[PDB]
Image 1 (tube, rainbow, N blue to C red):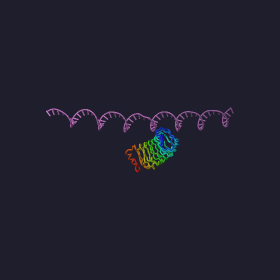
Image 2: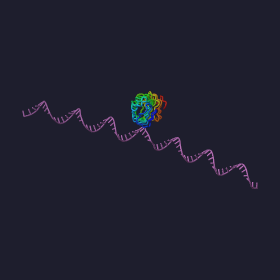
Image 3: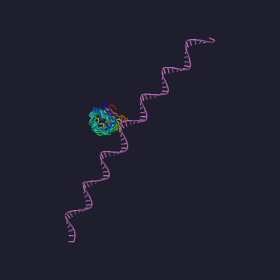
Image 4: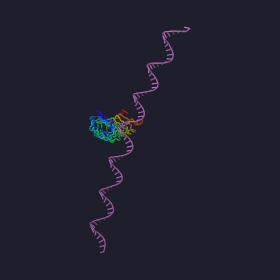
Length: 225
RNA sequence: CCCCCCCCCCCCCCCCCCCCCCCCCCCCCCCCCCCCCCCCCCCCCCCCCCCCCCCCCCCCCCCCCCCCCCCCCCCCCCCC
């Protein structure tokens, strides 16, 4: 685990996090490991981190006390894990995050409300998940959100009520690639506050569905398609 | 030569309630085993593409060297 300012533990087959590192480290990387559990009790010493890349590992579920100890954590990477369950208190105490990757966690459904308790989030990733609807909450949140990725999901319909959350959000990227959406609801994109870019790569529309898509983009601020 | 009415004690049967003890079924939680699917760690094997390295072979170019063939010149000498 070589580290001078950047802490790297890539491809080192770690089972538990190390406990001998400088306190003032900002980024700590443990990609490509098998941290089966990530206890919060081992991070008493680690309280000055900003980015935490713990992706490509085998974490089952997370605890609220993990980011209690981190008041300055800003990047939280959970790529290729088993975090299939989310709760209101999963990301409650930590709200300074501006980056949150959840690619390939086999997330099935968003139950009630995982993302109100943060307002400074910028980029949200939900690629390679089992989501079938774009509903991520009940009320309106993610005011400062700009980047949203939902590629390689199992979404077949893009309903207007599913995007009522983003009535006051400026979104520059809606990554909905590799999802077999076959129905478009009126006002689905008008519910979005500020839509700037739509990405529908590898998605089977056809000419008629493309025409309906363009009709649904009437009177909006889209820049890229 | 008889019936009736009171009372004690002990029975038997029947309905209700409360106890233990057990059986069957079911619920909840936990453990073990088997099967299916998925993720990650490595160490890899096979195939294709791309890039280089060595050696070698064919063809070509350039510079030659030797030999053969042809032509010209210089000097010397004869024939009529």
